[PDB]
Image (cartoon, helix red, strand yellow):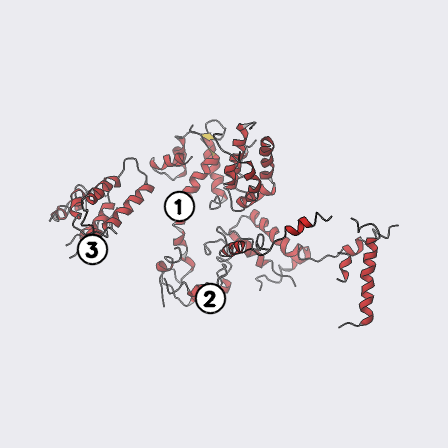
Amino acid sequence: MADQLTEEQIAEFKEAFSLFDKDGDGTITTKALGTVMRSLGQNPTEAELQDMINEVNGTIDFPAFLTMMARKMKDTDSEEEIREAFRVFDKDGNGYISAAALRHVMTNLGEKLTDEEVDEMIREAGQVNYEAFVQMMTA
Amino acid sequence: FFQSIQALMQTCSVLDLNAFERQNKAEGLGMVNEDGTVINRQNGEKVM
Amino acid sequence: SIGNIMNNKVFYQHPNLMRALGMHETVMEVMVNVLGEIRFPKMVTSCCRFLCYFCRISRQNQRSMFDHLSYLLENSGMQGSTPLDVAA
Amino acid sequence: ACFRMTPLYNLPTHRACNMFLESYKAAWILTEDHSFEDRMIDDLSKAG
Amino acid sequence: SAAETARRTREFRSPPQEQINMLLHFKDDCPLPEDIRQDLQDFH
Amino acid sequence: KSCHLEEEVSFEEKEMEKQRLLYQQSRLHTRGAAEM
Amino acid sequence: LFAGTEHRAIMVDSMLHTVYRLSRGRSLTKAQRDVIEDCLMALCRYIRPSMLQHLLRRLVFDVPILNKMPLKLLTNHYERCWKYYANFGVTSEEELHLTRKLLAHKKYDQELYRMAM
């Protein structure tokens, strides 16, 4: 959806789109779509721009323009949240995980699990590291 | 008066197995993504 | 009047307010009343395309537009968009 | 995704009050029991 | 060691809707001090 | 909700609280509300 | 399933040839590139190394001086690490050209070390 973007980037994406709107009617040409992206910082190749417009006369507006970089922001974070996951898990922040706390920290995680499923998810991963635990958790 | 209740008594539900396991698989999820909270009993009881 | 909503920059960042305004209801029946052959194809394509973009904003905005497919299926009867694609 | 959710104190203060009312409504307003219907129906009837 | 997870159920483990729900729970398991729980009950 | 005021005890109170309901029926059905 | 295909064993030489020239495309995106590059490493496994000499000509042509074909390097090191039991002189032919300029240090590093057969 359009929930993974919080508000302040779209507060920056509007006037970045509106300045290169050619007529004030909220539309742009197909070629200026890369030129605004140079001002954003994300500079993809030429090959990453046809499949944008192949997905959607050559007339692009702020409705269709949000759906491009929403597809280009989730993929830059969906494979990245597995890095930011483990930061409160262990003690010092390295990668080794004591299995003693993991038998009872998962029963008050807020998703309201039981003691049955958490025993179904510990021996299939004494001490299991950070990267085999997420390999059976991220599926 | 005796038409508008004989029409009501026909449109009263009984138990429904084909609606039952839909409510089970709906309850197979606990919390939707991006911190959205799932309304539990809004639709909730789908049978009866 | 529809097209100025498509870049107001607040419609794209307050999805709870837009259905509390009930603006998806009010744009719905103006498509219905012209539909009631076809009369005016240059607005039903422009209005229902906004509704499809409205459904793709949040979680519960899809939930709000979900209830009306009982009626939206009853108007299945044209190059461009269509109110059937709002149901899909 | 049950760990990456934000705490309160990073929120914009205009979004705290949006969910504060939705909490304050269903926990404090709706929980009150008021029984005005006893004395609305009789003075409307003694008014001959 | 073990009771810290009962404290750790909010700050990264409770969604911001359900955060203020349990913060607003006091009437008749609460993290609120006795001073700032009074001025609400002067408003209501 | 007006008539719902009644719907280890003894005899006399349990028919005393059968007229008080029956009075509340009398307040409301004598004014044509039965046909409504 | 493709292990044990001594019946028909020459179109797989033509199969494995044309995908490597399809592995780079003049008009292909990175999203489609990840699929064809995944099929190469999987077809490197589950096959006996008799037909591996057919493709082994084009592998060693101009690779170790550059680093627009790092995918071939991982394709190389996985084909001989599981073959520790001849045009193998081509490996010795690229046993010098890599260290000309000496980035992607740990991409072609062990590719020489796994070529040690």
Q: Which mark is residue A75?
A: 1
Q: Which residue is mark 2?
A: A115
Question: G49 or G104: which is nearer to us?
Answer: G49
Q: Chain of mark 1?
A: A
G89 up-or-down from E39: above or below = above
Q: Which residue is denoted by mark 3 in the rendering?
A: G82
Disc 1: CA contacts within 10 A as few (<14), some (14-19) or many (>=20):
few
Q: In the figure, A103 relative to G52: above or below?
A: below
Q: Nearer the viewer, mark 1 or mark 2?
A: 2
Q: Measured from the top left, where is residue C47 in percent x and y?
A: 54, 33
Residue type at the position of mark 2: Asp
Check the picture and name the quadrant holding the C terminus of chain A: bottom left
Give neighbour class at mark 2: few <14, some 14-19, many 20+ (Cα, 10 Å).
few
Asked whether residue G31 is in view, the answer is: yes
Q: Which SS class for mark 3?
A: loop
Chain at tag 2: A
Considering depth in this image, is D48 or G93 the residue closer to the camera?
D48
Image coordinates of residue A135 in percent, x first then y, are 36, 57
The answer to whether the residues at label 3 and label 1 have Cβ atoms under 8 Å apart is no
Q: Position of residue C61 (x, y in %)?
A: 54, 44
Which residue of the protein is positioned furthest toward the right in this rendering? Answer: D48
